[PDB]
Length: 239
Ligand SMILES: NC(=O)c1ccc[n+]([C@@H]2O[C@H](COP(=O)([O-])OP(=O)(O)OC[C@H]3O[C@@H](n4cnc5c(N)ncnc54)[C@H](O)[C@@H]3O)[C@@H](O)[C@H]2O)c1
Ligand SMILES: [Ca+2]
Image 1 (cartoon, helix red, strand yellow):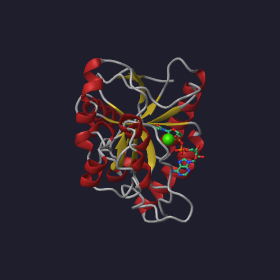
Image 2: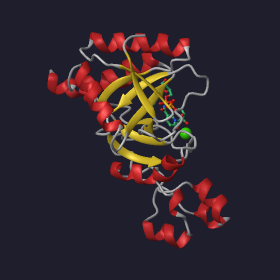
Image 3: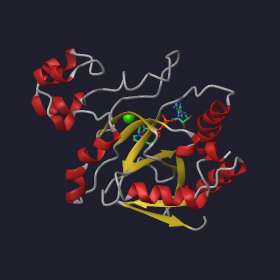
């Protein structure tokens, strides 16, 4: 089952640190860890084994990387989450938290993204150009040259190659200034789950993280606890 789990706890820890100090990786926070386990992770495991479908397929995550002072999405400071391998499938990346939702009812999920991922952020581009015509185009459907004709600055264009997210985030990373949560749509597989996110200041976060980690162990996925904040990712032995 090692081909499905992706390694033991020590191998996953070493994997996520290596990625964190290289090109980065992903962090998906979750308000309902029971739902994430039961309705996202477990269907993905069943599909890996040949049973069900990965119906949800695409999930939101933030890009994290050593030295990048990046916030995660946790408005009430009460979330746990998953540290997710850079090898998860990328459906699109934006530096803005915009309106891009999950796969809607009745839409085919596996290729909903990148096709329906906005190729640029309309709100940011409009504030920067005051170009009315931005709202007369389908942002999911424009090409590079249409974006040029609209005058869309590159700062507002989405990224579709993982290796290129770190180039996008290079200037914020160097300045050390806190950046708002960025957002990627990713399709993670069970083997891509490398760690459990813990906010060490939050009793809610730790209680939820302990339950999620125990639930994952029952399926043979033994994950390290990872305290991420402010461009540092550090292990917690327990809790
Ligand atoms: N979660 C992150 O790390 C992250 C990162 C960047 C931006 N955001 C933004 O935060 C807001 C909340 O997003 P979120 O990811 O916390 O919630 P979500 O959309 O992933 O899940 C919300 C709720 O819907 C269900 N759900 C979970 N995954 C689902 C899926 N794939 N399809 C359908 N239903 C699903 C569960 O009940 C869950 O509690 C959104 O605006 C999002 O763009 C979140
Ligand atoms: Ca959003």
